[PDB]
Length: 307
Ligand SMILES: [Ca+2]
Ligand SMILES: [Ca+2]
Ligand SMILES: [Zn+2]
Image (cartoon, rainbow, N blue to C red; front, side):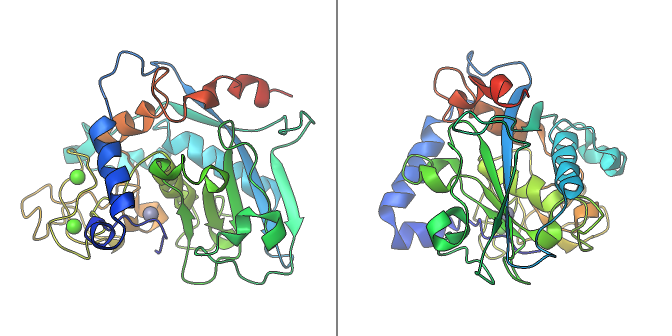
């Protein structure tokens, strides 16, 4: 598994002090136990931009709808494989109470099914250029990122499964906010290629878009980086595949060990089955009705997701 949304804090501090200051300011300013975090289901209008250079990349509506279903299961703890969560970690599992719905009104007020399809001469898209997010670079412009979650689906290449933009970048880069997913790994079963065939590449990416970091701290394997979530055990490097429970490492060397089945690890889709309650608090805090960076998304979410 490969994702382009690392936050290697040691590297950022050494090379980009303004970015480092923005992240530390971000972490100092989060108020998880605020009275103005909504208690109700948070509704997210989604628009999926299919950007395709061949027929394989022009994935079906059924395939896209299955991804929306997977997001609703994972973000509402309605995933059947929650039965796989070790009992030692089950008391920490969270229900984000976030719902996703394809948009039914586009930004100019036209009716839509929430899926855009754009043909392109670009053979492979680059995370560095973010070219998939711009019509003039062969991709497709984002839809008002204060009101829609944009999910681009394209050919990212054999190595990258997806990438997201973090919320601390929203103020400086609002037009590229959203998530990009490799077309081979979008939706559940169907055209999705094993072992990333259960729609978890988007769950993981959407977690980044909702302020979560890789559980091991993007620190090359050390015990020094953090994901800023206390209820995710300190972890060395990423886990891949599907380890056996319990897996201990040099950072958490006692049972129940590391939470390799967390969506924010790098394990196979079928190996993942939970967010924690700490991760859920972080995600929902973005919708704080007083200071939540994504609070405007709830104002017209109902109108934008009704035909
Ligand atoms: Ca942690
Ligand atoms: Ca680590
Ligand atoms: Zn990631």
